[PDB]
Image (cartoon, rainbow, N blue to C red):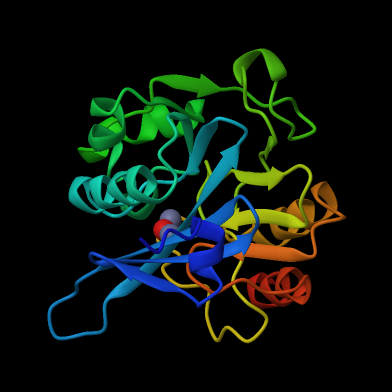
Length: 240
Ligand SMILES: [O-]
Ligand SMILES: [Zn+2]
Ligand SMILES: [Zn+2]
């Protein structure tokens, strides 16, 4: 008989759900966190977003696996119970696109950088259903991003990967750097095996310039931070 809203519940603090963690960042915006078990070592965390936009939900990034992504969808059903209209996934690595099959089975329309949709299938991953094309200035061509609501998608240039994209949430102070940006105390940029080391620093800067009003920077592999994360990341990336 105690029936708080999800917002009221998330005041208590971050919530464990199955093998995931959820955190409310602002009303109508939650961070999902999933973990890749690496035998003998600590599990690798990855963050994405869930946005309630009127009577629908929008997702940024899958979890590492289909099952973890199904757990995200279970949380949305239990706590929000609105249809998930679409998902945007932010490059062709496992932490961002490892759960595409779960999204597709749920009837969710999926979008990724056209380049991610080329890169993913040859890695044994599944492409998104729709491809985003970006103008030379980095902004998504609106015709390729129909019905995105508050999501503003920006290609900052090659960095963490050649295909990495970023997402601002209009009406909030939040911008999602995905795996491009690490927090202002990070001692490394993580696995740079697919990175463009020449352009990384400039791409981090371009993300900051694209979303100048975003005071909360959300990231895949760090907890949310203030804007100092952006220049810290660019400093770490300088002259790799
Ligand atoms: O990643
Ligand atoms: Zn990555
Ligand atoms: Zn990542």
